[PDB]
Amino acid sequence: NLKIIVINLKRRTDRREIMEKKFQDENITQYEFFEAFDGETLRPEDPILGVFKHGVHGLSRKGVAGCALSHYTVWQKIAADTSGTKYLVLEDDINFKPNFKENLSKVMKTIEPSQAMILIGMTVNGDDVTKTRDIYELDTSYTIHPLGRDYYAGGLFGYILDYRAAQYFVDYISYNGIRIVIDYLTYRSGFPMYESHPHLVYTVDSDIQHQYDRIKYAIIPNTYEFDDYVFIPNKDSAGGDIREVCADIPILKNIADKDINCVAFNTYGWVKNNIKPLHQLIDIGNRYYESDGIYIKKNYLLKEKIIINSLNL
Amino acid sequence: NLKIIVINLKRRTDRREIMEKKFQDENITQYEFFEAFDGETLRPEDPILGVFKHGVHGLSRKGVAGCALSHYTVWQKIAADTSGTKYLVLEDDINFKPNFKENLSKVMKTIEPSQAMILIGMTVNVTKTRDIYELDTSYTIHPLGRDYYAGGLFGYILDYRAAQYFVDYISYNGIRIVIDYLTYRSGFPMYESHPHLVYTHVDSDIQHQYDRIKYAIIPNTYEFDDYVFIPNKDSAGGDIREVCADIPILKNIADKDINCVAFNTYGWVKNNIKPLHQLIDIGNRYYESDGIYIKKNYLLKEKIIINSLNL
Ligand SMILES: O=c1ccn([C@@H]2O[C@H](COP(=O)(O)OP(=O)(O)O)[C@@H](O)[C@H]2O)c(=O)[nH]1
Ligand SMILES: O=c1ccn([C@@H]2O[C@H](COP(=O)(O)OP(=O)(O)O)[C@@H](O)[C@H]2O)c(=O)[nH]1
Ligand SMILES: [Mn+2]
Ligand SMILES: [Mn+2]
Image (cartoon, helix red, strand yellow):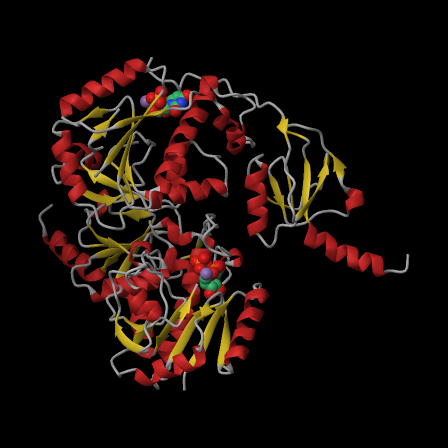
């Protein structure tokens, strides 16, 4: 049956105790705490941070990043469970509307097979709170609807999902890194989302909103050699970009593999459709890796090589 | 719907007149002047300066401080307007590129809901920047070209979301960064127009003034239910960080941080303090009196245990 996961910082034993007491009052015994990534203690050299290494600096805020890692890690776990078991993921500061246990039960019973991602709470646009009280607050049907995308102002504090949604989110990140705050990431991912009527949970004490310090990434070893690419350390081809992803070489290499139009990627996280002549590559210093540089597809270079060597120079 | 605000010193009536004539020439008929904080007349004892009272002394330069206060006050106003109305904030020495009114209109029409902070001009640190900033005729909105940025809050479009974020940043940090770079370093997502719509000894009420405000000592009238104040005492080290010598700001930071057990009025918030009998003497520098606030919950825990002991 339903697995409940509560994302909780080890240090927030206050929040943990509150949640445990809430579950007791609801007679819910089937839950577990996920030990949340503490943004404060994330190590600058930890390779898991690769997903955040790009030009959207807001994602490097310690609390923002820790939160993102926590949901993402939970998704990896859920993604692995292809049994189809349902998970309810909660944050550790939520409130239950009265008769939570009964209401959740009714909602669960109503779920159809295609409803893989369901918000049972969300932040509603301030301007839309009044006009959506009928569907979100006052409703007594306990039914599941397409997400009201026009009303959405964030929230992964209460959602029911299975491996299908989790795997999709995980896949999205493998092609994008984490360039969007984690709740908006699900919203922008293109995965179909649903909602309960009414909402079952709702949410000021915050380990995120007042932390503006960013993780300062340590330079980490570049131990990556690939059969299909030549690596040129400390050189780049400015421009000719498809897009920026994130400074994570395995992620980048895979993206480059899958894209016929991609001829090169740099370790800063740019995947490129055009590069300059090699003699026109510019110098780039180590920012993320020892060494940073550019990977170029061998097939591209081999074509050039054959032709250039044939020429009467 | 766009509200235009021009930051202008009351004394710079010359700049004001120029701007008004510029608006006329551009057929912009609605705008208002914000009365800029004159750094020259900021009172040493004015409590508003608490945000500048720290070790980054460059922020205490009279013009720098006045400018910072002006944008910050404008942000407070905008932050209050949660209707989502767009504001265009200008400094009072800018030039409009030809066909400003029409071009602005085109830019406004392209705005997406997440684009809360948009530079329509900035100081650029040349082929690429001329093409995107000067020659471009698309009138579209892009992520800020962070690599090209060399400052500027002389022309920006924002709503309450950007303003409130900046305001919040300052409530947790004071103003330890020149105000333009503050937005840039704040972590808020910033955008830019292609092209830019506006552009800027050189006439300046900031860049020639190196004299700093010398802060007067002001009364410490602050008593808090959750803290005991010990005047003219400090606990050396055990610091999280220095913020600024502003007691209300500090108290709020201390409230919100479970690891914080004390703060001094010099602007240091602390995670560890010595035994009380090992507190050191510190003189009045910002407040009468300077000293240390210690959380009562911390001391009450000690008190219970110490009183239980066979002494
Ligand atoms: O460094 C952090 C801070 C928070 N969180 C988790 O993110 C959720 C929201 O945290 P909080 O309530 O502090 O933030 P807010 O709701 O204000 O964004 C909770 O489940 C936390 O355990 C996390 O994983 N790492
Ligand atoms: O004491 C001062 C000096 C300037 N400013 C404002 O800051 C902006 C930039 O000032 P100025 O052009 O003199 O400075 P610069 O561009 O040389 O830094 C203008 O809107 C001024 O009204 C202010 O608020 N207080
Ligand atoms: Mn929360
Ligand atoms: Mn100027």
